[PDB]
Image (cartoon, rainbow, N blue to C red; front, side):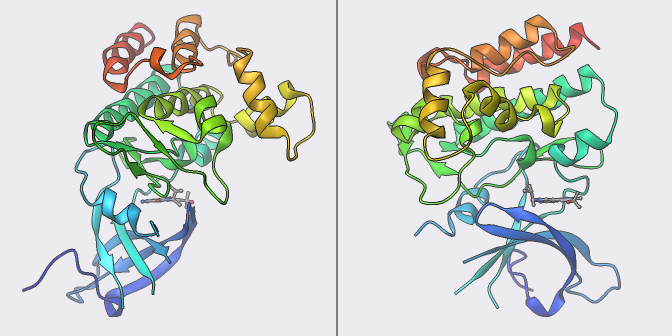
Length: 281
Ligand SMILES: CC(C)[C@H](C)n1cc(-c2cc(C(C)(C)O)n(C)n2)c2[nH]nc(N)c2c1=O
């Protein structure tokens, strides 16, 4: 008799490494607390100011399309225990599997469902990329890696953070690149980029950073963020992917409205994506 959210190191046996989450390596573990021979698979992220904020946030969320908090283990450091999403990320999935257009439109829809909820709870994700969206057994999107997620203070529209280390700047709106201000609408921009990725089946050669650097026309370096910002401010965007319908590119372009106030909300995007998914099913 005790708290299920408390995980004990003696019953966690590591199967393998899964990947590098932002601010923490994720691994796969078998948790057999009752020694019944089977236990359960779980994902475990090792964390070292806001270095716990991913646990603080993710434990307050309950939704089918957001990866589910299970508990913690601190037997200095901390291990976030999450559900194991067994098919991994879309970035590594889509290039290795054949996937139709409607199925892609359905993954996009699910992301919006999860993100509408997230924003309702007054959080921003700040890391919405195909790489951080995971598939379960039924090919259901679970949104993951809340390493950069923040609580938007109440009454406010954005949150200001200048990340001392790496961040996904090729998924980031100009206000993010320029003012380090992250609105709810900024996550919609990232979703837009995430949908571009979907439709390119995450071909690395067509990936947002590959594309954006070609368009900038200058080699990667200290001035890139500035040039990317000036490029996006001139209204250039990622190209319509091959065999992507015009109507679906328009959706991406609307999520890519330069000024953040003119972008769709995740609420607004849900009916639209259902209707467009229907049209191509
Ligand atoms: C969201 C990413 C950044 C992290 C690393 N991540 C990865 C996985 C995963 C990775 C794989 C492979 C294909 C082997 O690399 N699989 C099958 N699953 C995973 N599963 N469940 C989770 N919560 C979870 C996760 O967070």
